[PDB]
Image: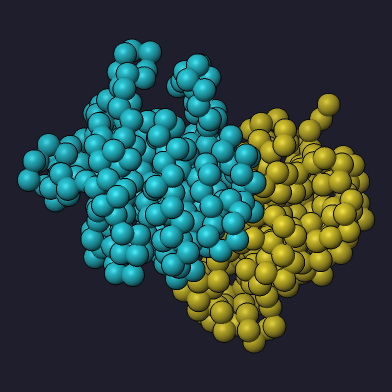
Length: 236
Length: 236
């Protein structure tokens, strides 16, 4: 019985940082989970609102992309790249074929995830069928408006989750940018929908939480842990 | 509430393991928090149900006690040992003089913490005063019967905590002992008092949670982080 994971990527790719660089998909937030799922025998399908995506340019730096990751990123024939090439649009997805819905991030998610009704329906269906919903970094942005098909309440209401920290936005000096673009942080979303936000000791620590079948991670360093947790949570 | 910490130690110190070794206070669960508090400018008072304690013999092994820790442990003139010499009984404690109540562990806590009503009242008072209640490893055994003075409900009811894992007990082969001695695991306590137990990915990982002013850690590897968390939590 083929075990499948639907890995969502932000479709937003545009100038964002003060240095003029663009945000978009944080490379390892897509690559590490991909590797973890593949290692465990899962098949992985990528998807974005538009079927297209761009890389967060800061995530391309050597500190965030090196060694085997860089090699896989550069090799056109890598499993990673060949799979990315087959990226789907929400309309091409059949929710019932997946056991796990994983939302990778990068600041780009703040632009499209909150309004991605079709991806939210897919995540909601996967969750209603006993599957797992997981998200790392700014991925929880997609929880804004995500409803639990069985209860009708926000899927994260009364749940414990983590995600990119407010302090992290401040340390990066992007908090003023978020305010200017009328974007909400992960902690903002958690507060709005009645979720309990639990923070890491430090903003860049590998930190993740498993609350039943809802799994969340804080940042790039938490991508792998988030993926591992989503696999383990299938028995929850 | 002066910058002072009350660090609780288990008073149980009897043969426990299959090899005949005794359990008791897990050295680094007392030492690491002690160093962290002292480093941040806090005065620290030790306390145990009987005013006495013994070391968990497995925690004395090189893998758990080495380097500077071993040096401080052996140095009879260390600030650690001089403070341990002044260990108090619950009756010699004034709850109003502490900002933080910290429960260190080792398997010994499973024997005395659940019935340590006097220490629980102290913890409850500190918490009611706006202070922090923290526990690491089996320390959450202290939460069995702990009441929130403001509501009359279990202090951990509706709260998210972590602590030593059931799987960890099985791996160590101590589950058979717990069953024989009619002891409850941390996860058992969490369920009995309405708390949400959030688990680490692996039983030995450095993992901790901050839920307002209630802080918890999973094991020896998490003692330092739990102490760090208890200090940062003083603003909740």
